[PDB]
Every structure is written in C-alpha cells, then in structure tokens.
Amino acid sequence: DVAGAVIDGAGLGFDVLKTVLEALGNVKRKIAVGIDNESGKTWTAMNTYFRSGTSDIVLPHKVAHGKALLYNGQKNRGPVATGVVGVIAYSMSDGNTLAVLFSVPYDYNWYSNWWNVRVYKGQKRADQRMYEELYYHRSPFRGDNGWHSRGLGYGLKSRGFMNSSGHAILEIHVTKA
Image (tube, rainbow, N blue to C red; front, side, top):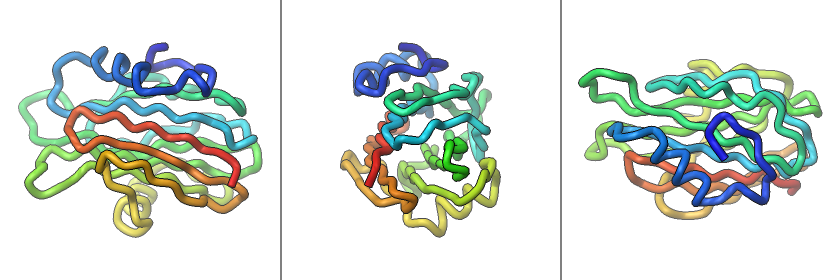
C-alpha cells in the first residue's frame, strides 16, 4: 500500500493515493502516481526522467497484467520555486514503451497541472526529448478534475484523472482498446 509497491490493479484508488501523498509530509509541490496495468502486456521499469523535482522511490520494476504500480515525487529541496515535472518509462512485453508525463508547476498564475500517456514503438528511456514531446507536442491532458480517455495505438487505451492543486494525485488505468 506504500509508494514502492506493486498492488492488485483493483486496489488502485483514491484512498491508496491520498495516503501515498500525505506520507510525503508538508512540501509545497508533491505528487502521488498510481498506474493500473490492464493492457494484457507485462511492464518492466526503465526510468523516470525528472525535468523538475525528485523521488527516492525505486520505480516498481515488474508490473504484470492486472497489477497497479504506486509512485511519488516532490519538488527539489531548498527555498526554490520549482515544482515536480517528469516522465516515467516502462517497456512492455510487446517490445514497446509506455511513457507517462506528469507536470506539477510552482507558479499557478502562469501554469497548470498536466499529464500525458503515450505508447512508443521500441524501448525508449525517458529523457528531455520525450518530456518535450509529451508536454509540448502530444496534447497533454490538464489536471482539471476531469477523467480523460484516449487510444494509444497498439491495441491499448488509457484513462486518467489529475487534480488541479500543487498537492497532486494522478490515477491512470491502461486497458485494451
């Protein structure tokens, strides 16, 4: 039930994610990510690229079909005005990559919460380029208190939800299209 964990997908929900978030203590910018694997593919962790902020969670290595991964992130230490922005990358047993963008900005006068889910062909580790694609070019969803669904190609689709505040919860379910 903690952030390093792989749980039964059916157990991924708001209450698991609220506890994962509050477990981070009182930081200005922080995020709880839950990703439910119902894609039929087995996911193996590659990496998280942090554009901003950090985590000391070991990215859950093996997420089989019907299993959810729990994860978290937070802004960098010190009196800096940055948020927590990054991309998570999982290789799937079909040879492709599941990439997940999350963006929790510091300045809510100029920016918003964003998230994205994309399938890449082959095994692409998360990096600055992938961040730019997911954030700037691939029509990311807004942390706008709304559910957003989209086909990913490769016989899959994603469904996610993200709140608007600097204490963010991102809930994603990857299923077959």
